[PDB]
Length: 139
Length: 139
Image (cartoon, rainbow over all chains, first blue to last red; front, side, top):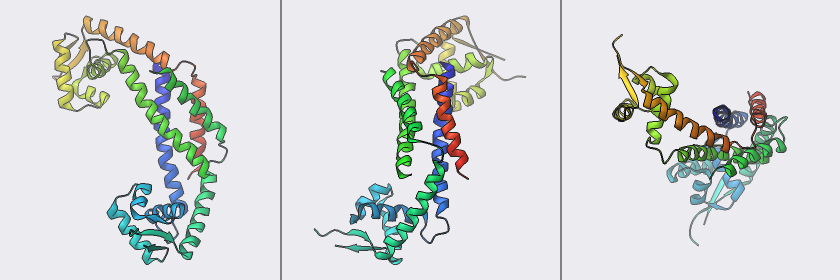
């Protein structure tokens, strides 16, 4: 199936390029807000896990120690998070952080709905099944 | 659609991991033959394009000049290809090269059919349509 291999290859290229464009689209939706994309990554991670250690945020966001330290410092200065004291340091949201994260999450969610307009869970599970078929076929 | 984004993300991971496994599977099918995987890449490219320049084989296979030069030298020594003389150098198959490439292509094709057993062109075009939908939705 030289032909089928061709069609699959087009799909692998398209899945990856579309994934990249989807991320850009969601980031464009909050472009006008005071919180930047990298600040949002950290804020979102804190909201999802609070109270959470600076070590664990790095793992969650896949950013290095220095990068997370830098962004956490900006978020503290913006009064969006608080850093409190075993004797290691945990991050959590302030009232202002909770307000802003809620506002941003809602905007991102609305754009995400637009992105998936006309696509159903079933549409996706059908292709996951094809990948399972191929995976089974091969040993 | 936090949920839908989750399902899509699982698909992007699975498409890429499955692609890698498919390549390994096809390479396993010819593991016992005298021609190695990297030699096959070059041989296949020559068969598909002969007579073809050493420069163009590099582009076709996405290998660098030194790598292609090395592999071409092995294929010349194995008497599978011939290098002949504007005044630049073109590669083509010998009778032995044509015989061996035909044998290998047939084995790979048979394994490729096994890989795609129960998967139809239609199954793939339906997901390409979903990617087009998402791509359209976003601007």
